[PDB]
Length: 99
Length: 99
Length: 99
Length: 99
Image (cartoon, rainbow over all chains, first blue to last red; front, side, top):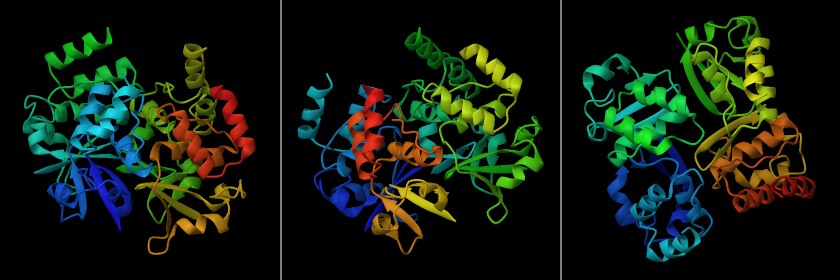
């Protein structure tokens, strides 16, 4: 499949297999992402920061590369990582690499 | 409840409860935002600055974090904060973080 | 009246009256913008640089201020201002500030 | 003829003749880009980085200007140049500007 993820009006579309790669995360776990599903529009909706999501999606697309865009402040971006439940392992790697 | 905010063609979506974080602002007060509403398309339309708005919306979503996008000059973002009536406190946090 | 401008897929919406302020420009002149009109979709289409268009739109929305976004290189932006035919004074005022 | 390129839900639109300015690349070659075509939607689909793609399409539109968007890191953008197969000539030149 493909899946549509709507971040505060900005629509993203990715393969189902892209998200299924990390099944423990919010987006990869069918039980966690269902809380954000909108059956009326067949999409997931998040009322959240928009610039961060390119990098959150690239984490999946790249198979594990977590990079903060230069224009997204570290505090904001770290809050999004935790929200999307990328995991402490992932955060670990990211931490060092940043500060 | 969901609300759509169209900034010069750029679509934003959020919840009524998110705008309710700051009820005395333009978007938070029904009386102030009502002149920009379009019942036909079921959205609010502003013929304004596109690159500024994701940070204005994120201010509500974060419960008060106002950060000027790097690509938007100080005086352009200053006018948008003023127009959206974000308040003296938001205007003081803007000043402090910019100089 | 409302006008839709599609820049390589990125849709901008503005009032016809916003474009009407500068009638010697490409977008303000009915005879110049007709070449890029798509009568099927009821929109103007430009197969051009996307990031520069926020500043083009700002020229109209601001009542004639021409400013270069920090992440758009000057050679690219200068080509875009020429193409949209914003004018000599516009460019000269732009030139000066820049240099 | 017009063509729609959907990069992770972000729809870019251009002309066939624009892609044909570099026939040896992925998007310029029918034999390479058809693997990403979506029969049902009449568009190409890439489950790839969004902010990189405006610069990739602009490379075609401009006739060879390849510039990394400030917000996209060097390694991520480099990977995109390779994927879209812009060529060794184009990559060499791109290496010079960053260093």
